[PDB]
Amino acid sequence: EVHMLDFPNIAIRPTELRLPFSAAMSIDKLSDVVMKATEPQMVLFNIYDDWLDRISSYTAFSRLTLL
Amino acid sequence: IRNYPGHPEGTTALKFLPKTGHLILSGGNDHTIKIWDFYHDYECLRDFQGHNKPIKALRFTEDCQSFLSSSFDRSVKIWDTETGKVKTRLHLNSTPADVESRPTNPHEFIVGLSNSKILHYDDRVSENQGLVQTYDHHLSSILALKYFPD
Amino acid sequence: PIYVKGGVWTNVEDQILKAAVQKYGTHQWSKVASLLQKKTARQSELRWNEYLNPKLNFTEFSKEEDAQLLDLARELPNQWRTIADMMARPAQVCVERYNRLLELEDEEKEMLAEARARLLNTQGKKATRKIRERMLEESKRIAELQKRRELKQAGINVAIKKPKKKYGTDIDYNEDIVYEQAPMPGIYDTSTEDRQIKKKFEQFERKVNRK
Amino acid sequence: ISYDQLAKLSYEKTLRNLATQKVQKDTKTGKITIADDDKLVNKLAVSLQSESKKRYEARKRQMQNASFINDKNKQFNEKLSRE
RNA sequence: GUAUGUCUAAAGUUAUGCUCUUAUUUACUAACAA
């Protein structure tokens, strides 16, 4: 809320529904990359690639959520 | 039982080649790395160093083609077995007391320092003059390291 | 599980309590209670007072003693602590006699191991910490020596760093004599002796160097 | 036994250990050089070391003889038990 | 989380019965999460 005061248009959403993203970092390659990191850097990824290609994003996200 | 006079200056760092290893690599306190065989006819092929200080920790790669070397003047040097013309690391903070390369891929290469900061150097990363990543969870001089053999 | 204390005195438990009493004495009942995972402070103290203390007695009463007892009952009506004191016995036992006259192991072993561990560990954290630091210090020293020695072997002579002196007037005792309080001035002459001892010293130094 | 008696009695003993087997003064300096036999002083040194050594080993034996917790307590209970 | 306490912070002083594999307890600890 405080660091979003730079720009007021960005609404905040407190999720009532807890999503598992502690376990998100226990995906193999992710954890690997985390360990690899040597400095203040970001290394983005497409959390689902082929799934997008096949089906809409929501479908992909359901699978991801399950995983 | 049987002898061989190698390095007239005191300290030495004698090590064989890996598994199928007919060779006796030494590198003493007389700032000169030397090469003798298991066959009683002890044949000398001296891998001369360049760096001023004596050579401390000598170890081979899994390939048996390049052996690492550490000295007191912040100088690690990789050394090709028979030829000896090869990648070089003249510059560090101060002496790395112990060094070891990876037992599965000769590329990765750990050097361990007195300041207690440990350093990677892959083959392309030795070309880069960089590190894959450092370690800093020991605080005293480490002088001691070896890989879990896998 | 946490719970309200009580129960019954298992013999092992009793023994443990006795040991504690030997250790900590008859007025630190909290500590002794703590030593017993089941039993309370109050419980413990009571037990010690009533059953466990060796300066009690449970020998049977002589006929004279019986007379004394029952006479006391007749005269002091059921003030059995007073009566007990008069007898010189513990009170419950006395009462019982009077009445007569008128007519699991894993857990136990856990507390045992813990107990013995405690009783054989008799130092405040300051002590433990201090000895820890001492051994660590020793280790550090030997490691340093190994470096220094290694370098000597290697041919680089490194003088051992002084202790980073805590204050301005902090003393190194090898620099010069501690507080040379000299001997009392010589009545008998001492010159030859001085020489001989000097030689011995220098010789010793030489030996050490060679060693 | 007082330290009076125990001194004289120990004096008497070491006299039996003896019974087994010149002065020059520079008065200006005050230095009283008693030149005496260097062999006898050496015989004192060796004997006195041997006496102290004998005593030193005597404790070592008595220490290795055997209701306590640690080294000190065992002895402290021994200090109570002797009474 | 602290008091507090150590540590580092670079220039070379002239000598020749056991091993093993695991699963369980209990304890302690934990400015780590609940």
Image (spheres, helix red, strand yellow):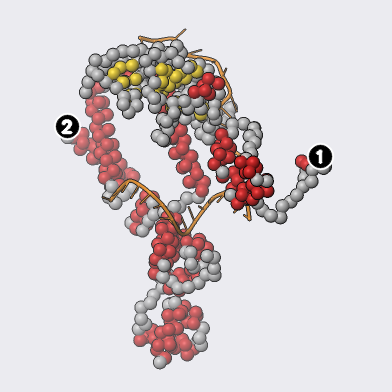
The reply to whether residue C142 is in sight is: no
Q: What element carries label 2?
A: loop
C74 with respect to A23 (left or right): left
Which residue of the protein is positioned furthest toward the front in this rendering?
A54
Question: Spatial distance from mark 2 to mark 1, Cα to Cα?
Answer: 109 Å
Q: Measured from the top left, where is residue B14 in percent x and y?
A: 34, 22
The reply to whether residue C58 is in sight is: yes
Q: Mark 1 points at which residue?
A: A7
Q: Is mark 1 on a helix, strand or loop?
A: loop
**Rendered image: mark on residue D21:** 2
Residue shown at the point (23%, 28%) measured from the top left: D43
Disc 1 residue type?
A: Phe
Chain of the residue on which disc 1 is drawn:
A
Q: Measured from the top left, where is residue D24 in percent x and y?
A: 31, 17
Chain of the residue on which disc 2 is drawn:
D
B83 with respect to E27 (left or right): left
Quarter-wise, where is residue B22 in the image?
Answer: top left
Is B68 placed above or below C54 here?
above
Co-location on one chain, circles 2 and 1: no
Instruction: From the image, state whether disc 2 or disc 1 is nearer to you.
Output: 1
Q: Which of B130 and C63 is in front in this view?
A: B130
Residue shown at the point (41%, 35%) measured from the top left: B150
Q: Measured from the top left, where is residue C3 in percent x and y?
A: 54, 68
Residue shown at the point (51%, 83%) measured from the top left: C79
Q: Which of C46 and B98 is in front in this view?
A: B98
Q: Which of B80 and C68 is in front in this view?
A: B80
Residue shown at the point (27%, 20%) measured from the top left: B38
**Rendered image: mark on residue C205:** none
Cβ–Cβ below 8 Å for labels 2 and 1?
Answer: no
Quarter-wise, where is residue C196 in the image?
Answer: top left
Total numbered labels placed on residues in the image: 2
